[PDB]
Figure (cartoon, one colour):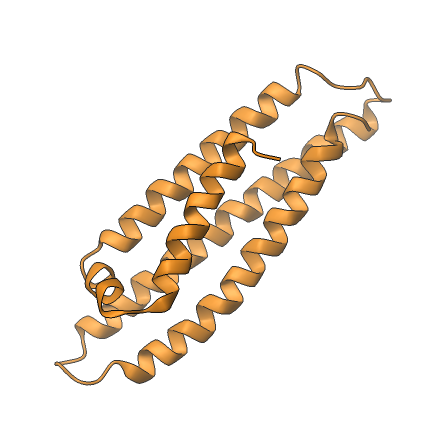
Length: 144
């Protein structure tokens, strides 16, 4: 429904989708560290906005028992952490690819790319399921 953190994650998604095409332009930016620097910036923004959103949501909560509340808060924290780790895993996999190409001597990277593409598809599935889980928890977090 358009929170700042969701827009930030949206930027991350848009950039990752482009990286996933693995075109020659992508490959240029991967080999420089520009892609991983960009992903780190987008990741950091998302996390920052997520934490700020949670803090604001806490200004308007339905008062529930409190045992429940401490647990909803812990579960939300866990969900936030998962999103960050997921984004970092994407960046890390790209760092690994750059190292592999740099040790490659001008040889074909096609196989490396086929493997990277398959791996990123699975990393994206994980980040998306966690993002959806995080959103669901946030949406119900005010009530208890």
